Image (cartoon, rainbow, N blue to C red):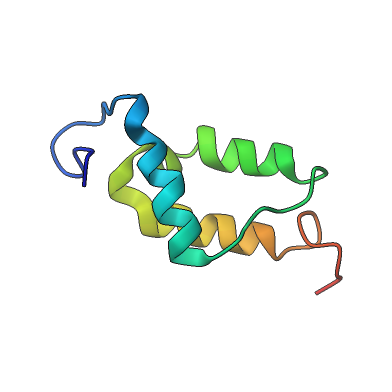
Length: 76
């Protein structure tokens, strides 16, 4: 894509492509404000969601978050 997937870890602020891809790969993961902090750690700390190469691993890691009782009001 616009980022180096397999070349270098560094990507410009145009890394917004990640959010665009993930939201379409998984669907609406827009979560709860209670769980907002977990999403922010799982998006900003994890090499999955930072580095554009690991789009799939990020996507799954967010999905299981968005559907677990912290992001999901409904008890699964």
